[PDB]
Length: 133
Length: 133
Image 1: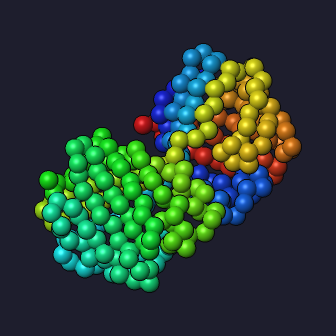
Image 2 (image 1 turned 90 degrees about the vertical axis):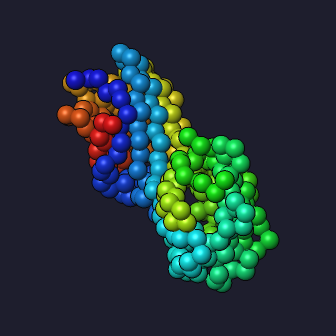
């Protein structure tokens, strides 16, 4: 059949490295792209194709209990080992990541249907806002 | 409320660059990460947290008609300009990406509930298999 409509999820990807290396794509990009899984959405109407591809990759799995200090390896970032401790301050989830970096941690809380997360490291502060699906 | 269960989708992300730069994350990685959108799934049971974060980024939007040659900028790869032409060979969707790279293109077809896609460039062949959600 010539019908290719539908949402397709990548289960296999052989030799992406060699393909990208032939496209003169830099090493640093290839190191990331090989960890990606694509999801192709094809809207086909006759010979008219509309395709949308979304690369993604599952990551940092965090299991912890508030009050219990746990070891953490930031494999999703700087790959450093930090001793994290999560506590409650009001309704705000406060974490302290003790390690090489000074003043490292994050604060997480809920306001309305939105989740706020402030990542802190040194003097830099990163504010992230999420919406409840 | 201290309840933070649910699937949260990132709508805003301020100063991710400075945060990662403080974590000594290399330039090449930061250039990619700033184009990411996270999706955090939080399974909270009392003080027990189970969170799963999935970074993603929508990409290469391809609209074409079989038989009609169109201009294509591979901004998702080598950022090269190629003149693509998609034709039917049986039930197989065959494309030729004319440009600097020799023997560049891809073949796409359906077998069962799976979509097969072979990307070709030079002597390297990349086979990708998708499953119908």
